Structures are given as structure tokens and as C-alpha cells.
Image (spheres, coloured by chain):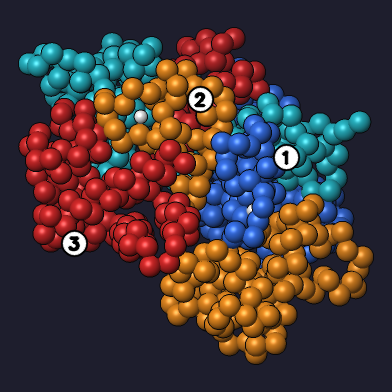
Chain colours: A blue, B orange, C red, D cyan
Amino acid sequence: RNPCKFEIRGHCLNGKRCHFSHNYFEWPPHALLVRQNFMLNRILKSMDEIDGAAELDRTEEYALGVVGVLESYIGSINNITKQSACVAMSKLLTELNSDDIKKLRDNEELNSPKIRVYNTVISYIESNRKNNKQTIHLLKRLPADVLKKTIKNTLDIHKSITIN
Amino acid sequence: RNPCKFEIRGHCLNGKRCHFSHNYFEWPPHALLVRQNFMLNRILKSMDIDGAAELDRTEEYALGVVGVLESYIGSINNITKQSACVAMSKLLTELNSDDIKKLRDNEELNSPKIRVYNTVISYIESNRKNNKQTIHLLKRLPADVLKKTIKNTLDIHKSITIN
Amino acid sequence: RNPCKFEIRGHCLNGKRCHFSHNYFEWPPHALLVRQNFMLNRILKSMDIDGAAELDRTEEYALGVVGVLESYIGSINNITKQSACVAMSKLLTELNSDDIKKLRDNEELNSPKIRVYNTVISYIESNRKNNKQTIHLLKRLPADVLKKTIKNTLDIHKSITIN
Amino acid sequence: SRRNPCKFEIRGHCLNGKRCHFSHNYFEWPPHALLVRQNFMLNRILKSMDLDEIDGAAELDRTEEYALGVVGVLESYIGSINNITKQSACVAMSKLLTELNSDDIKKLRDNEELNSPKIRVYNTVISYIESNRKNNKQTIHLLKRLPADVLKKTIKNTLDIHKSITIN
Ligand SMILES: [Zn+2]
Ligand SMILES: [Zn+2]
Ligand SMILES: [Zn+2]
Ligand SMILES: [Zn+2]
């Protein structure tokens, strides 16, 4: 029996009617790998009303993604408000982890000015983790030009961690 | 030594009496894949009202949540409205928004599917915040609109899974 | 670089002094599979009374939960009732209801197994809600019925695992 | 003729929406990429159920303590080098305890002949692991109260156990 495609994404809800395999011992390895990923996504999601948030769920902000949203706010296109960009920034911070930044920080010569930005981003990541609503509120208070700098730095760090 | 079948499903509870391998470094890859699945199931389960207890009975277990809901829609197998609403909460828990958003994005604008996708998305998010509340709302819907909503959710569930 | 054996079991704590690979992209698949298992064990552990401390002593550790329970049933190895009830809570935690429901469904109606399966299922669910409460209930049972219940739970545990 | 997996998705969730040309579809990924992602995701799940409230903690995030690691920090405190305070060493010890698990120590304890003096250390470390798991802030406070020489002994024993479990 082939693996049940519902079970591959989580739990088959079709009871005894379902004729596919729900028995992990007989599944090929690829299906067991795919299911772990869907399940990890669900577990992570299950352990995660503010201005600008609902806008990120609309058709064009979905297509932009959090990065497109933030890059758009920087270039003042696609109608991204500041509120939305701050919410998006919180989402970006949630996706980063400190340890990867510390690793970058450690490759810097001392008194490199990058070190200051790395530490700023690290503190944003930690604030965001403690209280993202608070962190978002702080971000909205920043002058536009410094917000955009901060975003841009965070975006550059996000790209560089991922190509190393 | 072959991997211990108890350890493959979680944790071997047989202490030193057990002669099988509890050492993941010597397991074949297939057994380490199977165990990860049983362990994820357990981790997910470990972080989880009228009509609920009924879903644990022999025939509702055989129907599954989808059988229960489909049965309610066709008024067979003695499924009460209360039970169907609980079962609907369980279906919503199994879905995720992001998959619906992805479907929503394939729609041409002003497609009437978009309205249903957004309705289901809001039910998923309510259910995640407070499933007891979401269930109570569902019980208040007129039977015919409840059945519509269930049916739409079921259809979305099926189509996500065949793409 | 070979994978770091500390990272394989969790997180390497040796900073930059460690010369082994902490980069998953370069690991062989077996090491990535082994690490997932150690990390799942850690995640599960991180989201977890009279007779409890005894189960951590040298000989109860060697017996395992099942040894402890089997010992209590045969009145050997100095297992108190309190301990056996704690150990029973741990056995219940390791079982899951769905597997029992599957067994229950293979039974002809009015089979006396059905009554035991449902009893075990309700114990599993009580234990999941409140294991301290479930342990207290177990302590209140007459020895002879406790031993029956334990034995039934042990038999179900063995049969689910050989099918 | 198909798409390579998205490197962002491999480390978590791609945040580039539809602009991204790489595959976000696990059904078409090679197994190695699915294996790598599971590891990044488990790290994230574990991190998300976890201190800068407490003295000595913030110091462990600085450039040189990061390079030393927890083990370097503890070994440095023992040898009185690299400017590790007692406070920091206690925080680091809490982190080391978090990484260990009791069951492995119990297994070591079971290999010992009775009245072996190792048994006493194994049980001390086991109780530290369990205290730390219940309340790490409390455990850290206790550790700060120990006389330096007994703290260093305890740290050293814990380090040795940590090494030996990992080479068996
Ligand atoms: Zn199925
Ligand atoms: Zn075993
Ligand atoms: Zn290492
Ligand atoms: Zn991508």
C-alpha cells in the first residue's frame, strides 16, 4: 500500500474508509522525510489585533512576502504603510536566530562598525522573542529614515547568513 | 543488535532486561525515520464539552472526523449537531491557513471562492485561539449554513491534499 | 570535516575551539537522522509525590518501568504500591489511545476485552490530563484489582508493539 | 528539469513570497535537504520553549565568551583566566546541565561497583540536572553560594561526565 497523502501532511481523518497505508514501517523514506517537515511546521506554528498586521494577509502582500513588503517600504512603493512594515519586521526577526549573527560578529576585526549593527539586530531579535507586540511598537516610534536603515541591515544579514 | 521496537515507538521501558539496541548510532536509517514520526506525533499530541465524548466511541472512531462530518451532512449514523461541531474544530486544527492562502492566490480576482477561502481561514484562526469558543459559534449556526461551511472546509481539505 | 559528536546529541558547547563540523549541509544523512532523535527526546522531555524518587534508584532503573510493574505483580524486588502506581502513570504516558481504539475495533461486540480496552483508554486520558490525580486513584484501588489493571495494560503494551 | 530547494526554506520558512524561484515543495526535494531542514526546525522548536534578568548571563553573549563556548568559559573559570567571573561560570554551568541528561548518567552509575566514590558524584550531578530543569534561576543562585573550590570541583566533574558520555 502506498502512503496516505493525508497522513503525509499530518493525520488522516478518514477513519477505516481510507485504503492507504498509515503504517510508518512500510513507508518509503522520502515520505517519512516529507511528513516530518509538515509536522515540524505544525509544531512550530502551534507555539507562536495590532495595526498593519491584517494587511500582510492580503493578496499582494502575500505575493511580496515579508521581504518584498520590507523592500517595498524602503523604496516607498506598493502601498506599504509603516505599521505594516514594522509587523513584517517582527516576522523577519522571528525567522532569524542570534547564534548565526554572533557567528558573523566573530568573523569581524575589532572596532569594525558592522559589530555595532550585528549587536543592534541581536538585541531586536531578543526583544522580539520576549514580546513582539512591544518590539513592533518600538519600531513604529523610530524615525522613518532610521527604521529603513535598520530594516535594510536586517535584510542584508538575513541574505548573507543564508548564502553562508 | 536490531533496534528495539519499543524504542522505535518512543521509549523502551524494559530497563536492562531488553536485549535490543537502544543506541541510535547503530540503527539503520529506516528505523530512525520511523521513530521520528512516532515521536513527532507524541510531541504534537502533548501540546493540545457537549458532543466531544461521542467522537471517542467505536463507530465515530471508525468514521473518523471526516466520516462524522459527512454523516452529519447526510443525516446518517446518528451524528448530532454538537458532535459535528466538535469534529469540525478537529478538522480546522488539522488544516493550515498558509495552504489556503496559497489556494486563494491562484484565484482570479472577484472569484466567489475567495470569500469561502477567507471564511475558512478565519475559522482556522478562531479555532486556534479558542476552540471552545469556535465550537460554540458553530453550534449557533442554522443547520443549513453549518452544513455548507463543513462541506466547504471538507472540499478544501481534499483539494490541498491532492495538490 | 566530520560531524561534531556533541552537536549530534544536541548543541556543541565548545565554541570555536571545536574543529568538527557544526554545519548540517555537510553532514552525512545518518548523523542528521541520529541528531533528530536525540533532539526529539529532548523536546519531549522538556514539556513534561510518594513512590516517585524510588524509581530513580539504581535497581528500579535497571528494572525499568515494566520490570518495576511486573515485580510489583509478583511481589518481588521490594516494589511498594506507591511506586507501582507512579510507574503505571509512566506506562500510560507511553501508550496511545488510538492504538487501543484500533484494537477495540477488531473485537466482536460484547467481547469482554472491550471493557478492558475502554478502561485502559480512560486511564490513558486521565493520566494525560492530570497524572498526579490518576496516580492517586490508582493508589486507592484494592491491590488485586490494581494488579489486574497493570497486567492488562502491560499486555496491551506488548501486543501493540508486536503489531 | 526541476527546481532546487530554497535555501531559505531549508533553514525555516522562505519569506520572499512568490518572487522566489526556488522550490518550496517538500515532495520534490532531495532527501538531504529535507534532513537538513528538520535539524534547523528542531533547533528552532527547542529554542522557542526556553536569563538576562540574572547576573553573569549577558557576559556569555559577548564576542570572546561566544568563542570560548560554555565549556571554554567553565574551563577558563577553573584556571582563573579570560576574565570569567563566578556569576558567569554559574550561568554557564546551568547551560551545561541543560545539555546533559540524567538517563545517561544513570547508565554510567549502573556500571559502577557499589561503594565506588564515582557514585556520589554521579548522584550529585544528577540532582543538579534535575534542580536545573525545575528552576534554573534557583540552581544558579545555589551554585553562586558554593565556596569557589567546591564549585570548581563540581564544574570539573560535570565537564568530565559530559566528555565521557559523548565518547560512549
Ligand atoms: Zn488515510
Ligand atoms: Zn528495548
Ligand atoms: Zn563541536
Ligand atoms: Zn524561497
The residue drawn where x is 91% and y is 68% is: B109
Residue C137, numbered circle: 3
Which residue is tagged 2? C34
The residue drawn where x is 43% and y is 38% is: C162
- Mark 3 — on which chain does it sit? C
- The picture quadrant where one finds residue B64 is bottom right
The residue drawn where x is 71% and y is 56% is: B98
Q: Badge 1 local density, few (<14 within 10 Å), some, or many (20+)? A: many
Q: Badge 3 local density, few (<14 within 10 Å), some, or many (20+)? A: few
Which mark sits nearer the N-terminus, 3 or 2?
2
Q: CA distance from mark 1 to mark 2?
A: 21 Å
Rendered position, D28 above or below D16: above
Which residue is tagged 1? D26
Residue D59, given in percent of the width and then of the height, sits at 40, 30
What's the residue type where badge 2 is placed?
Val
Residue B161, given in percent of the width and then of the height, sits at 74, 54
Is disc 3's CB within 8 Å of ligand 2?
no
Q: CA distance from mark 3 to mark 1?
A: 47 Å
Residue B34, given in percent of the width and then of the height, sits at 54, 35
In terms of depth relative to the viewer, which is nearer, D16 or A159? D16
Q: Do circles 1 and 2 both sit on a common chain?
A: no
Is disc 2's CB within 8 Å of ligand 3?
no
What's the residue type where badge 1 is placed?
Tyr
Q: In screen coordinates, is D39 left or right of C90?
A: right
What's the residue type where badge 3 is placed?
Leu
**Disc 3 to disc 2: CB gap under 8 Å:** no
Q: CA distance from mark 3 to mark 2?
A: 39 Å
Rendered position, A150 above or below C112: above
Rendered position, D120 above or below A70: above
Residue B117, given in percent of the width and then of the height, sits at 76, 69
